[PDB]
Amino acid sequence: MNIFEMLRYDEGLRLKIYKDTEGYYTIGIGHLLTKSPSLNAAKSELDKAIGRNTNGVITKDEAEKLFNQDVDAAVRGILRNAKLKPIYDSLDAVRRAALINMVFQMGETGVAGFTNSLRMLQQKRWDEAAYNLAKSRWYNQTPNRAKRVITTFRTGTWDAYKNL
Ligand SMILES: CC1(C)CC(N)CC(C)(C)N1[O-]
Ligand SMILES: CC1(C)CC(N)CC(C)(C)N1[O-]
């Protein structure tokens, strides 16, 4: 297991523009295109992201290229953020993947808003952190994914992904 595998499971793979769990146009492995309700705007974002005029459909290789860029962008967002970087630095590699997963789903600003959870993670109070992370819109809106990510923080293992 690694972060690419983890997010590939959590996000799936779709080669045509679709709507994500919040209703936003997305493609590939969870690549958010826009929050605009305009499909034309989303298609323009896709063309710009891929570098060619698309019909709203990309190849698997193109989806994986965007995905690697997006994982990198999630790590960059963590490392440039004064609240996320010290937490990330304090974590083992499995729990680092859990934090990257959250930032991939919600963005740097959103995850940096988990102030009290971040402090508990840095303190390595894993069960207390797990409870606090569940008191969130995130957990209520995507509970199965949040449970997998929280189990990863709680245990430092890939147990929540093993049978998947
Ligand atoms: C690519 C795929 C099918 C995604 C799953 N979410 C996890 C792993 C184990 C990596 N595999 O193989
Ligand atoms: C303190 C701790 C370990 C955190 C859990 N998330 C919830 C309760 C049941 C309150 N427990 O046991």
Image: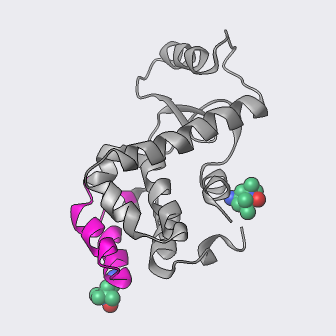
Please give left or right for residue 54 compared with residue 122 in the image. Answer: right
Give the magenta part as a residue range.
113-138
Front residue of this view, candidates 86 and 38: 86
Front residue of this view, candidates 90 and 55: 90
Using the rendered view, name the quadrant where residue 124 is placed.
Answer: bottom left
Give the image's coloring scheme. one colour
Which residue ends up furthest to the left in the rendered image? 116
Residue 129 belongs to the span the image colors magenta: yes
In the picture, the quarter occupied by the C terminus is bottom right
Please give left or right for residue 142 compared with residue 136 in the image. Answer: right
Residue 137 belongs to the span the image colors magenta: yes
Q: Is residue 135 above or below residue 78?
A: below
Which residue ends up furthest to the top in the rendered image? 53
Q: Is residue 40 above or below residue 130?
A: above
Please give left or right for residue 43 compared with residue 122 in the image. Answer: right
Residue at point 65% right, 61% down? 2
In the picture, the quarter occupied by the N terminus is bottom right
Q: Name the magenta segment's main secondary structure.
A: helix
Residue at point 44% right, 60% down? 99
Residue at point 62% right, 74% down? 158
Please state the horizontal and vertical placement of residue 16, each as a whole percent of the image: 69, 28
Please state the horizontal and vertical placement of residue 52, each as a whole percent of the image: 67, 11
Ligand 2 found in image quarter = bottom left
Residue at point 77% right, 28% down? 59
Front residue of this view, candidates 25 and 2: 2
Residue 28 visible within the image: no
Residue 110 visible within the image: yes
Q: Is residue 37 above or below residue 66?
A: above
Please state the horizontal and vertical placement of residue 45, each as a whole percent of the image: 52, 18
Please give left or right for residue 55 compared with residue 116 in the image. Answer: right
Front residue of this view, candidates 109 and 81: 81
